[PDB]
Length: 161
Length: 53
Length: 55
Ligand SMILES: *[C@@H]1O[C@H](CO)[C@@H](O)[C@H](O)[C@H]1NC(C)=O
Image 1 (cartoon, rainbow over the protein chains, first blue to last red):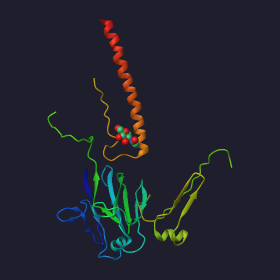
Image 2: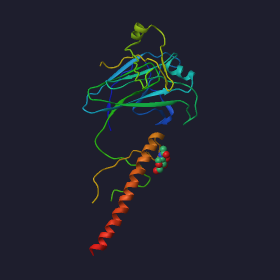
Image 3: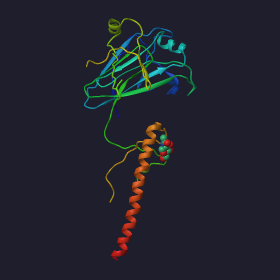
Image 4: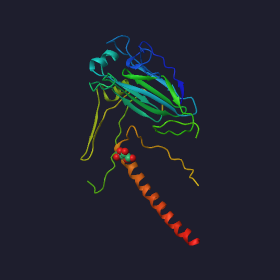
């Protein structure tokens, strides 16, 4: 995988969303995703639209996340009140997503979930992320390198045979 | 009424903006419900900007 | 003389695939296994008749 930065800028919203499940010298998050929040708790969230153009000569593995919070007092704490939406479009793709809060079972100490989705942006195509909350934004798009093969095993690797 | 299956096709419009969906179908939350004796689904439009095709 | 056709992984031993696609893969792999178990047992039994008869 060859990671290539997207260069998104964020105007007036928080970005350092962290959690206690991802322990990396304290409380952190994913290394290639951002958790876009409001400026403080229970504050509003402006409607945004960010775009990326695949300039290279190969398909680009784009990945974004949707946050399904644990409560309805948790979704409003981090993206304000109201009904939220994430719209994702391309020249070969169109879908849209809506967060769905609610309690569920504790995994790693939390009851919220993050749904990761993906598409392969064709060369000289454009992806667009309309959102107003519950969006785990991408940071670096990914590109494939060549040909290999993947196995699943339980024994040790030997470099002699 | 005929003695053969019928290929029914409908479309759902996902407009480019929220000022575009309200221009052509009014304000509010919209819905399309489609039912049959062997089928049941429902659809909701989702406006928002995307790339120009 | 070994084949040059590379077969890759379509199942998953850790996180199981969807059940309707997990049964089409399982039905197809048992069908092909019946073919290569028949052809191996036929070829060995046929070349034992040829080895005995040539000597
Ligand atoms: C397919 O067969 C394997 C045995 O190799 C089994 O572990 C797996 O559960 C089967 N899949 C389904 C969907 O039955």
